[PDB]
Image (cartoon, rainbow, N blue to C red; front, side, top):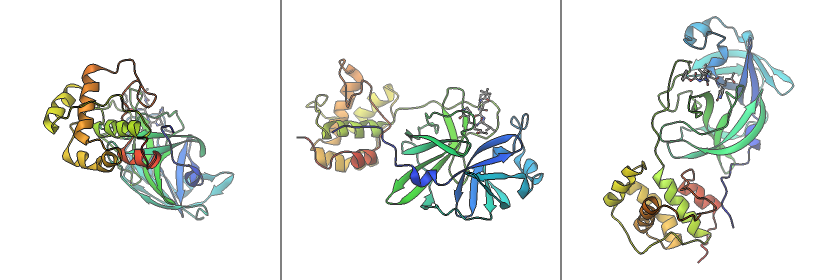
Length: 306
Ligand SMILES: *[C@@H](CC(C)=O)[C@H](C[C@@H]1CCNC1=O)NC(=O)[C@H](CC(C)C)NC(=O)[C@H](CNC(=O)C(C)(C)C)NC(=O)OCc1ccccc1
């Protein structure tokens, strides 16, 4: 049946994207009820960006300094404030399309959908995983700040990321919707580098289970391993140590497939040491780590291909 890096349907979020302008700087904002959220750096300029003092910069602005556009309609800003690295603009109109929602702070290894936006207009959507080093490998150009990351459960939209910047290695950094950054990054153009990254062990294992669920058992073996023996191979290959909580999270998958977690870890340790044989797993030649156990259950058949 297939396995694809799938994003959540984006409609509920498209209806909340707006454009915000300050002087010469334009970016995207998120319009929920009567508030528009956006990167606070929209109040920056040419040199403002290396060493901005936002408190200082902001006291110099008025509600009318902000130009909010909801499609073709102009939104009148009736108050403003700064919350960590975001600005909260109150506006006179309440977004008619606001969906049920909440703000969440996603954890390293978890995945979400990103709605790339430009000038308040949605451009495309893809799934990303929050990397252990707190960056995400997205696809963003200038104009994309304020684009959001989210998950949907039932008809509730859980926003979890707002884009703010790109680091030297081409990776991306941003904040949750309270404006607190993921990672040790700050919104100023002083040199910063992403920390060293690791492979997300739990996801790679979840992906092997998915590979087995829609048939495909070639990489399995008759061995098993203990957690520690596994973790010694893991350290060697720059993988995150596996833990008992991780072993427990893989219970449902384990059960549905009839393959013990440590047997799967034994399988993974062999893959790590013996390479792949020019063979592929779920159409892939590398071990994928951007799918959570949750993502696998959501997408795969609730019935294994025995
Ligand atoms: C959105 C802003 C708007 C108005 O939409 C952009 C998104 C990025 C553009 C390219 N890809 C993106 O994701 N946000 C920014 O441009 C951001 C504004 C700051 C936080 C006020 N700045 C950066 O993302 C910046 C881009 N890199 C550079 O300018 C150079 C040429 C210096 C590499 N990244 C940055 O400043 O990182 C810190 C840093 C690391 C290493 C050396 C120097 C600076």
